[PDB]
Amino acid sequence: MAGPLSGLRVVELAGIGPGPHAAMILGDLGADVVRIDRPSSVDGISRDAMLRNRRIVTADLKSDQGLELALKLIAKADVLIEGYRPGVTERLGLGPEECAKVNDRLIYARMTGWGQTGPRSQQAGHDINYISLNGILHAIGRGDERPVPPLNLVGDFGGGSMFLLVGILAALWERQSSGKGQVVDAAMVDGSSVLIQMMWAMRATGMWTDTRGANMLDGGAPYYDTYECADGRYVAVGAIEPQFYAAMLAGLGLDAAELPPQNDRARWPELRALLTEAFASHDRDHWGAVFANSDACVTPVLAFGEVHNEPHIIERNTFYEANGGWQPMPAPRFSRTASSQPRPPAATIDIEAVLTDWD
Amino acid sequence: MAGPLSGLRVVELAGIGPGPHAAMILGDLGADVVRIDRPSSVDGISRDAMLRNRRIVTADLKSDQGLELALKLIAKADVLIEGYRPGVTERLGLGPEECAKVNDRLIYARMTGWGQTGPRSQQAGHDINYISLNGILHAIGRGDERPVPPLNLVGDFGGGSMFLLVGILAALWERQSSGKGQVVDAAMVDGSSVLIQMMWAMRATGMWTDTRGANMLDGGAPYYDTYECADGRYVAVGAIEPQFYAAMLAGLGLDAAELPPQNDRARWPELRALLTEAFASHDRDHWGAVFANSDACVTPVLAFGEVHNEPHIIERNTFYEANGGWQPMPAPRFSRTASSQPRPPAATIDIEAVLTDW
Ligand SMILES: CCCCCC(=O)SCCNC(=O)CCNC(=O)[C@H](O)C(C)(C)COP(=O)(O)OP(=O)(O)OC[C@H]1O[C@@H](n2cnc3c(N)ncnc32)[C@H](O)[C@@H]1OP(=O)(O)O
Ligand SMILES: CCCCCC(=O)SCCNC(=O)CCNC(=O)[C@H](O)C(C)(C)COP(=O)(O)OP(=O)(O)OC[C@H]1O[C@@H](n2cnc3c(N)ncnc32)[C@H](O)[C@@H]1OP(=O)(O)O
């Protein structure tokens, strides 16, 4: 198995959203990942590409034998991932303390939205809920409209799976000097708050307000926003630095002397109207051409179905073909121990086989 | 120094965006982080809480002495972070090959948007540019409007700094076997693409379309979206699973018999009209009460300024106070080697004093 995490052994108790994602990335980077699902759900080779780089086994964890088989896996592993509500693994007899008896070296990684304790800790929830409570969701969207969810990228993945990964891998490093595992408590409401630390920094220096649509990076700034083009497609402009901003104006054909200052916020509506008219006068592809090799920070906004046709994407092999279609290659990339292309979701294998394999 | 990364030594070539965010989190978790800025840059103690858990030092890397003091720090460190365009560290004589000659244990961490090669590798950009090229930005916002940037959360941080962190820490694990460092190439265009791997999976199985605002998780579903309340504030609804959805309906006072099926997408206009009118009939804090302790997946949409009053936030200490504003405590959390509260930004330190200490 190629990648820096060759020889890492991971047991994943099947769940949804962040835990599978973290498991995936571990797998991507060459960890040996064994996913325990319940026999009721698994039937067929799974067509969820998020289950790439896995061995799937079934086991009724509520049975004596299913529990037993699972504790045998965990005894042989470096990391356990679970994404259930607090208390769930404990009642299965798979809680931290039961695991520490069979393996004091285990990294015990708990992925929740609300955390291990506190008043919301038993509430069901999804991404949109976790980001609503800590200020993030309120800050996203246009000012005249209700907030819009940024898919499930910020709570589940950015502020979720990624912090679970950082914790699993930091704990493995700590283990090298201590000889011992420990519990990683990754809550999406926490991770996503660190994810957005820059806004909390800016609010304290009076450089970010709670008004939606009125900030440098939320779409309020005319030089950091999307613009509709003559063909109804979009460009993105991200020209924060005055040098880049100047370059954009020149390529739009706009004389900086006729315009309000870049950062005079009271005249942003006026500046935006001038840029809107300019961008609207040619199609997206025209602007992509005009600004190629430029520091103007103007890029075409591609839909998923167009990404395979973009030279920069193709030539760096950001994607590989599978399946129905394209999927992202592992990230990040490593010079010496490089990841390989992901292995598609495997047939269900028997849990005893795995134990043989793992002695 | 508290936390799981106690003992880890980090050199950070001062940049913007993902690089400092990654360096912050390493510091947050106990790493010993030393940040080399240019002198034509630092003018007192920093106002920027992202530079917490750091020692700051000054050095003209274009001079011979600067270069050599920097190579001395790097010789004694576990990790280097740089987020300049490709070729900047090479031309400075701090490239990977040069560092490899003074410390072959080094994790050499390169944070870019476009990557180390290819047609766009030299173009300036920010978060919005990197997520524009890989399909992400186009998927964010209402169907009746142009795409809206999800702040800089998805390219800079989720798909940038966090992938840099994973790379660094994965390479440290690998170094346990090999006794050798290596280069980590973290590009925002790649990391953000793995961040959205779900949508690429669903797209393949016909469960996600390229039409903005017409999917289960983008605002198209009436049961996964925000709703304006009587007071003009908002709640979030995330009631995907039928049992949570049924719990939401009961709290709203709508009988299921009077509504279209939850997932009959052809009747989503009617369903949205019904939910819209119901949520609009009381204020946000009403709904927050009704649904607390519930599996209805209805939560108040709080503004930054109100977060510090939310019981669940207060009690788990998600935030700490510092310099006229709250900031987030480190994440994730560790049972035995807990992180401590972050140290504020300090006055600059002498690069010699650091080499000594090390
Ligand atoms: C649509 C998805 C994409 C979007 C996802 C997001 O936006 S974020 C993802 C969702 N949020 C989270 O993941 C946060 C943490 N998880 C949760 O809050 C919760 O798991 C949930 C709300 C998602 C779902 O609540 P549920 O009540 O279904 O599940 P819960 O986690 O409480 O308990 C799961 C039950 O399955 C049982 N169980 C698990 N594996 C088993 C196995 N192999 N064999 C037998 N039984 C098994 C456990 O023993 C437990 O039983 P008991 O009944 O005895 O206790
Ligand atoms: C907080 C602001 C916004 C954050 C929100 C976002 O979306 S941020 C995402 C930003 N994008 C990235 O970080 C992606 C990768 N980085 C970049 O593309 C680029 O750094 C950039 C476009 C941000 C900025 O381009 P510039 O052209 O300013 O800088 P570039 O990195 O090419 O070169 C840096 C220059 O500084 C010099 N340099 C750096 N440190 C030095 C030191 N201590 N003493 C002397 N010289 C030093 C280098 O030698 C080089 O100069 P010479 O060329 O003269 O030799």
Image (tube, coloured by chain):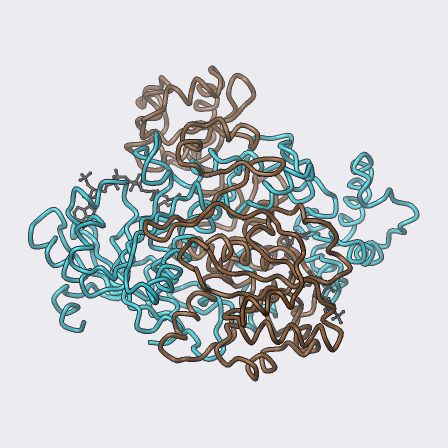
Chain colours: A brown, B cyan
- Please state the horizontal and vertical placement of residue A300, each as a whole percent of the image: 46, 27
Q: Is residue A16 above or below residue B85?
A: below
The quadrant of the image that shows the C terminus of chain A is bottom right
- Residue A302 in the figure: left or right of residue B301: left
**Residue drawn at x 72%, y 49% as measured from the top left:** A44
**Residue drawn at x 59%, y 57% as measured from the top left:** A20
**Residue drawn at x 72%, y 54% as measured from the top left:** B283
Q: Quadrant of residue A36?
A: bottom right
**Nearer-the-camera pick, B171 or B132:** B171
Q: Quadrant of residue B30?
A: bottom left
**Residue drawn at x 67%, y 39% as measured from the top left:** B205
- Please state the horizontal and vertical placement of residue B287, each as a whole percent of the image: 74, 58
- Please state the horizontal and vertical placement of residue B162, each as a whole percent of the image: 43, 54
Q: Is residue A147 above or below residue A102?
A: above
Q: Residue furthest bottom?
A: A101
- Please state the horizontal and vertical placement of residue A22, each as a whole percent of the image: 53, 57
Figure quarter occupied by ligand 2 = top left
Q: Residue furthest right?
A: B257
**Nearer-the-camera pick, B162 or B345:** B162
**Nearer-the-camera pick, A44 or B260:** A44
